[PDB]
Image (cartoon, chains in turn orange, green):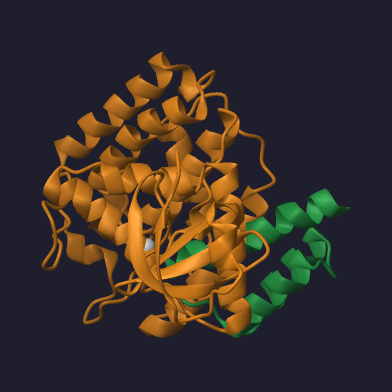
Length: 289
Length: 56
Ligand SMILES: [Mg+2]
């Protein structure tokens, strides 16, 4: 048994159903098939029990055409059709945080997630704020558990989108940049600080806020600007920001603060301000109640 | 129908986004077939046939 058994000897490429040993061709083809699987997955009925079974069913549908172990957890020994047996009870991180659950810690953690969702009835019959506070605890825990050999982020995100949908809310992760995701997660894992993650879940659940970030991202694409490496967020109620006026749109306006993009509602600007405001102007904005 | 276009738009945006959050950009044939379904010029059965037949 060995973690090494997941990759072709003398390479860094994961054994796959296509037999691609060249890393980038494997990535493009696995990416292509996983796109196909997500579109079709969007057509299945939502489960009655959100649990570890459902998590593994999602991973299995995403990666079944790529990996023999689609849907298998990494601390359970998996035997390839070639005869070798792989597992990775400990998956070390280069340079990173407190890292990931090890071995039996994965198992315990998943049992806990199973118990919690079950006693709280899949987080249903809650308001949006209630749902988000519960969801955040489960999301941080699944972040640490990281139970699959590969594809953990994609499976977890789909799990929490569908979980919110069945509880009558939404989580729109396509509005979150790679930068902001990493800031929020390491604030949890490193500093014990939940605020960035709570603010993340608020921006992508609040309908008023989703409209604003939708417009901003749409503009960025039409501009041909890639913000995946920058913080993008909606101004928090009561906070003040000071920076460079970035322009305005039908629904919202953008502020630029030490490289970050801060989105706010146009109706919250003083109309005596909006009138003469030019891109590059230095403005201060306090978001209201 | 508009509601359906809404659904598929979100669905392709989510596919693209969830890879970008891993540092992955999709192959241009992948983006072309996805965009044809979001528009959509293609039913889901046709979109699946074109994803199956793409040569990367
Ligand atoms: Mg991955």
